[PDB]
Image 1 (cartoon, rainbow, N blue to C red):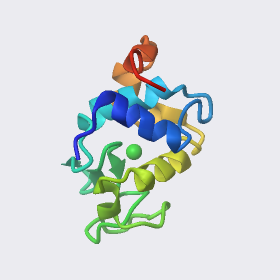
Image 2 (tube, rainbow, N blue to C red; image 1 turned 180 degrees about the vertical axis):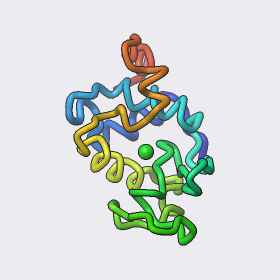
Image 3 (cartoon, rainbow, N blue to C red; image 1 turned 45 degrees about the vertical axis):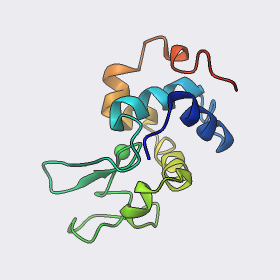
Length: 129
Ligand SMILES: [Cl-]
């Protein structure tokens, strides 16, 4: 599922991401845009062998199990494939755990480099919320 900007904003608000640990809704939509292009089926291998999954590109090294990331962890206690679903509940709840890790949304490199310090409110402008 490739989300519409406002469709995704609506979905994340309903799942309580708006100002979750201080991050206004526009941050999460900005992050999703640059991490996955709003595509729940997005995947990206990275160098250490781990793989990023889903609309928020959650990493298998710590957060989900994909059966091919030796010596990793599964802190969200889920199969990584669950993160690819058209229903973002899995990704959102797992993200909630991540943004609580102590490092905030800096966990997402795309957010740090492309959303942080920008007018993130523009990502939810014009949306019925
Ligand atoms: Cl991540």
